[PDB]
Image: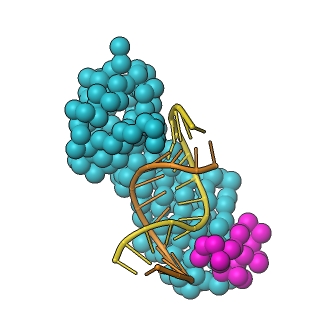
Chain colours: A cyan, B orange, C yellow
Amino acid sequence: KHPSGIVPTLQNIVSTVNLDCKLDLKAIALQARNAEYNPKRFAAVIMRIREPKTTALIFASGKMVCTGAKSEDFSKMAARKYARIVQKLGFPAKFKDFKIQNIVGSCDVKFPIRLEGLAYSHAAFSSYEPELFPGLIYRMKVPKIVLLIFVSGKIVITGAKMRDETYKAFENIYPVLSEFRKI
DNA sequence: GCTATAAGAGGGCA
DNA sequence: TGCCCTCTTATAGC
């Protein structure tokens, strides 16, 4: 399952759910101390909980975005709590169409990488402009995932809606990273 | 903090 | 249209 012997650590999960009822954002920002509401800056009530440590963006439409969780289960668990906070605030909040929208993972191959050489041999997938951003942007097509590769051997993998895409994307890149190890 | 990456949701504007 | 608005998170050089 993990031939490299390295398993990317999940760092951030973004999920969405439909509370299925219109929400009064001022009433929420007023009643719940946990919330922040700034209409002129952003159309959402920003609310946070300690466990699982997450941040929710709550919209008048009843739609909700949940960010910050370390796993898919934690994200859904956090979403459910926010849904309950809203219910208790006096809204008929449900939990419709919960969905994991993005998974961000990271790992360390423990060896430096020759980024320019990797970029050159994979021009169609790479974007490496160190003066702009020190990491190489690798847009993997299968699976459709974006990896940020640094000289240190540290790797960020983002864009996955399923964790196996994070894993597979890493496994695909591993042999390439090795080929371009900095001696 | 800023630079870059993915993804969601919405109001607002060119 | 079509993108920025906000927010999260790892990464690292500014």
State the image coordinates of residue C9 (x, y, percent, origin top left). 56, 45
Magenta residues, start to end: A25-43
Residue at 48 percent of width and 53 percent of height: A13
Is A65 situated above or below A50? below
State the image coordinates of residue A162 (x, y, percent, origin top left). 35, 52
State the image coordinates of residue A143 (x, y, percent, origin top left). 26, 48
Queried whether the magenta region covers residue A102, the answer comes back as no
Residue at 72 percent of width and 76 percent of height: A29
Taking depth in this image into account, of A136 and A159 the one nearest to the observer is A136
Where, quadrant-wise, is the C terminus of chain A in this rendering?
A: top left
User: Does any portion of residue A155 appear in the rendered image?
Assistant: no
The answer to whether A117 appears left or right of A63 in the picture is left
Where, quadrant-wise, is the N terminus of chain A in this rendering?
A: top left
Queried whether the magenta region covers residue A33, the answer comes back as yes
The answer to whether A169 appears left or right of C8 in the picture is left
Residue at 54 percent of width and 58 percent of height: A67
